[PDB]
Image (cartoon, rainbow, N blue to C red):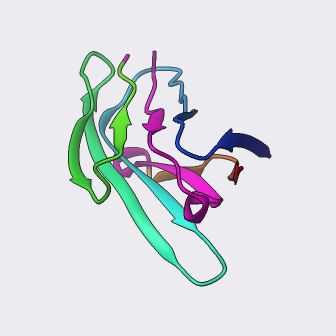
Amino acid sequence: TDIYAVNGTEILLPCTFSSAFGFEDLHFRWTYNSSDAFKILIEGTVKNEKSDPKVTLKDDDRITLVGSMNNISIVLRDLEFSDTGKYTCHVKNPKENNLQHHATIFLQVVD
């Protein structure tokens, strides 16, 4: 679904997971898709349900993890019109052979 944000401001793009019985070695990835580009924005690991995420890839310095729920939300600051597009959070649980794709967020940056 759609979120609107003003050029030059910041926006929080949310991602929460929950685990019935915890987890080990969770991996996450946020992606961006536009009509002509794809970007892996940030990737990381979470050792278990009692650990903080560890970022292993960040390709834009305007992105930060929000910090903790079972939360891998990101804040994107200093928005530009080219930031308009589709943002998707993906969570992989190798041990459970599980991969969840959260609903794509269409961010529209406006003047």
Looking at this view, is 105 or 49 the one in front?
Answer: 105
Position of 53 with respect to 83 (left or right) is left
Could you say where residue 100 lies in the image, as x and y percent from the top left?
57, 49
Could you say where residue 44 lies in the image, as x and y percent from the top left?
28, 46
Could you say where residue 11 lies in the image, as x and y percent from the top left?
56, 35
Query: What residue is drawn where x is 67% and y is 40%?
Result: 5
Looking at this view, is 91 or 42 the one in front?
Answer: 42
| Vertical side of 34 occupied by 62: above or below | above
Query: What residue is drawn where x is 40% and y is 25%?
Result: 66
Please state the extent of the stretch shown in magenta in the rendering: 68-96
Query: What residue is drawn where x is 59% and y is 84%?
Result: 36
Could you say where residue 70 lies in the image, as x and y percent from the top left?
45, 22
Q: Is residue 81 magenta?
A: yes
Position of 100 with respect to 50 (left or right) is right
Looking at this view, is 41 or 94 the one in front?
Answer: 41
| Vertical side of 59 occupied by 66: above or below | above
Query: What residue is drawn where x is 35% and y is 21%?
Result: 67
Position of 108 with respect to 49 (left or right) is right
Furthest residue in direction bottom, as rendered: 36
Q: Is residue 62 magenta?
A: no
